[PDB]
Amino acid sequence: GRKRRQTSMTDFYH
Image 1 (spheres, rainbow, N blue to C red):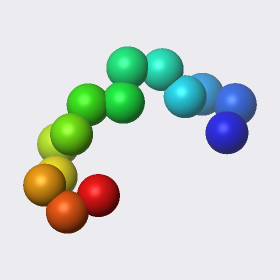
Image 2 (tube, rainbow, N blue to C red; image 1 turned 120 degrees about the horizontal axis):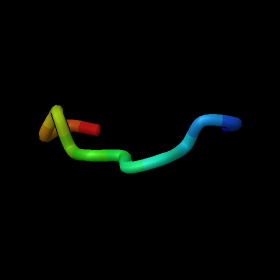
Image 3 (cartoon, rainbow, N blue to C red; image 1 turned 60 degrees about the horizontal axis):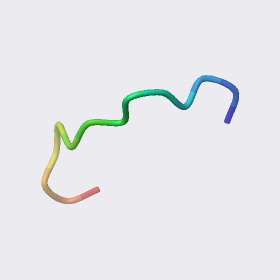
Image 4 (tube, rainbow, N blue to C red; image 1 turned 90 degrees about the vertical axis):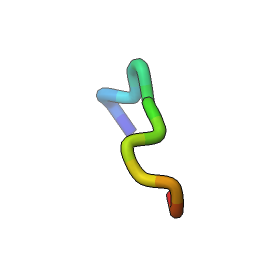
């Protein structure tokens, strides 16, 4: 990935 930044859990299945 080239835009991995602040990966919040906006889905509790990923």
